Image (cartoon, rainbow, N blue to C red; front, side, top):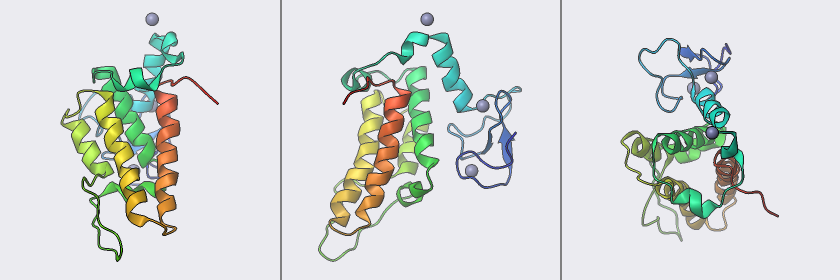
Amino acid sequence: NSNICEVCNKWGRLFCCDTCPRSFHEHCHIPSVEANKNPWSCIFCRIKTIQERCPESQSGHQESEVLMRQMLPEEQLKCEFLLLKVYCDSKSCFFASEPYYNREGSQGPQKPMWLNKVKTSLNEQMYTRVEGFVQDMRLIFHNHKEFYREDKFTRLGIQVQDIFEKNFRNIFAIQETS
Ligand SMILES: [Zn+2]
Ligand SMILES: [Zn+2]
Ligand SMILES: [Zn+2]
């Protein structure tokens, strides 16, 4: 196994996957690393199994159809994995915890949102459809763009949204377009 956490790239108290060489901090993995279960398989491994069991699941899909899917176990897993892929980028730090808004010439968003809130919402099974999860994720970046206006810090939102969007298209096998 790797000697650093796959998500945050630090050493520490790591749980090792049994079916691949990745390792994880307990709360870096999503869902949090399970208490027992020998062997244990990480989320990367679980996602690869879904694909292998149903190769046709990689054919192209329309975003509108994906969003309306109910959050059954496989879609829950896919959203957890997409969330984890965002945390994998170090620029996620900016969006992880609860924000506050006091900048001359700007007013804070009407509906603040942040990664750890989305993480809790998934853990608590608060989303009934994929659309719920995707809306909250895109709201994080949209709030940031609106608040920071012409400050160059707005770019951090564009950057982490791009990671989200690329991973959304990959994990849910969105049909490629020009
Ligand atoms: Zn970690
Ligand atoms: Zn694994
Ligand atoms: Zn099949």
